[PDB]
Image (tube, coloured by chain):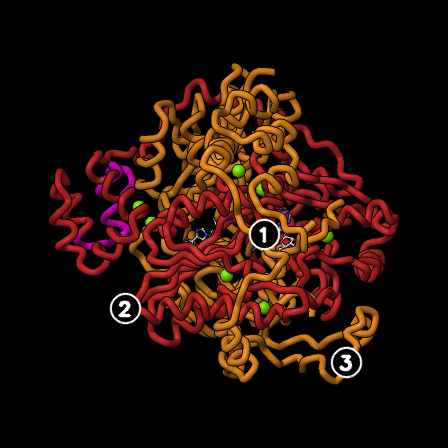
Chain colours: A orange, B red
Amino acid sequence: KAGSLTIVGTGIESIGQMTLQALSYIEAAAKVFYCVIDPATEAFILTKNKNCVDLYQYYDNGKSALNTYTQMSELMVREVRKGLDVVGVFYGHPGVFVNPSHRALAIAKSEGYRARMLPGVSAEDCLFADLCIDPSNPGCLTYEASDFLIRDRPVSIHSHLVLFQVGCVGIADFNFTGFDNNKFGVLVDRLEQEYGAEHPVVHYIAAMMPHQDPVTDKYTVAQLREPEIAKRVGGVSTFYIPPKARKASNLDIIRRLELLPAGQVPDKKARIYPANQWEPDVPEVEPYRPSDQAAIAQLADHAPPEQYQPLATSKAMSDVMTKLALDPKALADYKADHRAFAQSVPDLTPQERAALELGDSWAIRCAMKNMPSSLLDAARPWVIVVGVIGV
Amino acid sequence: KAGSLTIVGTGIESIGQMTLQALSYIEAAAKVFYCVIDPATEAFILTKNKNCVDLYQYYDNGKSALNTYTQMSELMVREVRKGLDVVGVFYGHPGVFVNPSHRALAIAKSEGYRARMLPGVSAEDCLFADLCIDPSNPGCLTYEASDFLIRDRPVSIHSHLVLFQVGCVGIADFNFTGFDNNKFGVLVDRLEQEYGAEHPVVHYIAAMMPHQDPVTDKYTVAQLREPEIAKRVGGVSTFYIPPKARKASNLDIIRRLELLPAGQVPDKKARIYPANQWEPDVPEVEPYRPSDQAAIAQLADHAPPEQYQPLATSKAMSDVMTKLALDPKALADYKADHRAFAQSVPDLTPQERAALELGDSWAIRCAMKNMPSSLLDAARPWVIVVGVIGV
Ligand SMILES: Nc1ncnc2c1ncn2[C@@H]1O[C@H](CSCC[C@H](N)C(=O)O)[C@@H](O)[C@H]1O
Ligand SMILES: Nc1ncnc2c1ncn2[C@@H]1O[C@H](CSCC[C@H](N)C(=O)O)[C@@H](O)[C@H]1O
Ligand SMILES: [Mg+2]
Ligand SMILES: [Mg+2]
Ligand SMILES: [Mg+2]
Ligand SMILES: [Mg+2]
Ligand SMILES: [Mg+2]
Ligand SMILES: [Mg+2]
Ligand SMILES: [Mg+2]
Ligand SMILES: [Mg+2]
């Protein structure tokens, strides 16, 4: 069935936070529809495709957001129904606090068209990077501020809390000059109830232009009642609220997971460097403990272990794998007929050609890496473990 | 002080999910250190810089993950201390479940070097895109599975739940052949306690190669006890657990936010299209209600409103804004001296040159967009509202 809809993001910071694949789909599309919030990103998009439409022109003062979203979605799906490869482009991650992307994709999918959303860099992704926090330690609760209030969503004082749309509390209408955030005090009351007047709240605004610095301003909950401080919270503001305390381990789980030395399970307040610098009353953690120093001393005698798999590929294979990631038309051709595609790629070795003919992950990997004899294959599979994971 | 550390991500899907800015830093760096999980991405990186080191060679069987992380961080910071511009590259978002990035950046920052993490596309970002869910509706709780168990982290049956590292429950050591996930039953017990035996759990694995499809398999909690099903959960598996019910609105908040018609506040089970297709017993929602049809009918008579700001820029300005986003060396030069940089860009109009000299967001925007008279400036500022936001 002719026609496709691919929805992509621009990320938050102008131009640079777009993914390579998002760019390649924008370039390949027959028609591009976009909704972005800075003109440099807009201009950039217009250099990449000749047939773009700005969706922002469908907003209006007093016009219901839902009617705007229905219209934005319909403009995209109308072109899909004509048999065109259509790309929608939205700020950030195009499925994070975005209504028309989900609507348009769901319609396209239900009518039998190819439909896909590509992920992008969200404001929360930026927040993690700029506030130097890992959502994994100690978990992350993420809400829209009005939804948080209206449905009385639970906080955990032991985990990260992230609140979107803190500059738009309770606001229903659209307006081109933004909104008077007159119900912000309702949010502050809730934060006082949950955390206390002296608990920190970090006002976060990611840099939107490449040369700008992020806003990373720590206030007390009580400071948010001051008019001069409240005034700073706008339409691109997010709040990060750090944990008030650390949660203890559960003895039953320690025992069932066989973390057998129970005295040597760390104290709940013990930290792996670095500690969260936004949490109240967190002790300084030593970066170079004797164990760290001993690990560093081992670097002089280091050799890769026997099971390590060196890259052993070719220019031809690297080129084709790159083309498959960066050329949506090549990818579609490959997906339509693995064998015909694989047989038309010049300079591939027999193993490379065979691996591509199959399309199997393991086969492609074994073609591109020297899998050693030492690594006796349990595949007849890997694990990441690059964080403070398990125990 | 000479030297810098920039940590960047590759995203999840091979090559294509790297951001433009991540690529530009990889190309500009004096030394690149990387930890990625597929060889196509590895090969790609090696074509972009002549001085790369694979951090994965510092893992070993039985060697503590913490010693590995200390070593990985130290390898990067050692080069920073020599005055080099160093880039670390990690799978996904480089601050999401990654220890050595945070460690290395914190050390570099405390010793007075330039230090920054650039966000990337995480597994959660992929999950939102592939499962067609918006974390904003009805909020999203995100945990590491072992941490979830050991610290008895709270679930909300009314919000999204995302669990990372479900294939590695309680696992401490590294091993090149992955892990036997023998304590998976401890996770399933907790999920049964919180949600019930018949509640859905979505096993999610994002495509890692461009031609692959994601795994999006719905099981009951009870089905996860079957050995053939449990076996499928591995090191790149994430669980998504949808809400069991919808949460009602709070009358006090409705009243304080002046959502004045109380009878016309939607029923808690009323949905904006599309509904979450993973939730149990969710009714079909009509995409084309009479209100949707009326909105679509208005498209024929549409003209952009008076307050809409058309792009009105130049090739010279678009080129420089693109260069600032995509050339870290140009950006540093610009940041060091706005005026000297701005005065050396040829073909800029006087307004464009002046806007760049200042560096102010508003000034750059007003140089690139026709700000109409109708939009009488409250700036002497915008809001997004592209989702089901406020009310
Ligand atoms: N520059 C910025 N810094 C911090 N938060 C931002 C931001 N831009 C947008 N946001 C957050 O996102 C909300 C807009 S809703 C759109 C979000 C976008 N799709 C994304 O992926 O993030 C804002 O109210 C704010 O909470
Ligand atoms: N292809 C994939 N699909 C779904 N989840 C994945 C994935 N690859 C990694 N993950 C999740 O991430 C964990 C690895 S920890 C590293 C996460 C990475 N920095 C990121 O940004 O996502 C896994 O246990 C799994 O829960
Ligand atoms: Mg989504
Ligand atoms: Mg908190
Ligand atoms: Mg590839
Ligand atoms: Mg592509
Ligand atoms: Mg981070
Ligand atoms: Mg849930
Ligand atoms: Mg720019
Ligand atoms: Mg750049």
Q: Which mark, by number, is residue A261?
A: 3
Q: Are marks 2 and 3 in contact (CB under 8 Å)?
A: no
Quickly name the residue at label 1.
Answer: A309
Kindly indicate the quadrant of the structure image that contains residue B273. top right
**Position of B91 compared to A58: left or right?**
right
Q: Position of residue B228 (x, y in %)?
A: 85, 45
Residue at the spot 39% in from the left edge and 31% down from the top edge: A54
**Range of magenta residues:** B357-377
- Nearer to us of marks 1 and 2 is 1
Residue B361 counted in the magenta span: yes
Q: Is residue A189 above or below residue A291?
A: above
Disc number placed over residue B251 in the picture, else none: none
Question: Left or right: A29 with respect to B248?
Answer: left
Mark 2, residue position: B2
How many callouts does the rendering have? 3
Q: CA distance from mark 2 to mark 3?
A: 45 Å
To which chain does the residue with label 1 belong? Answer: A
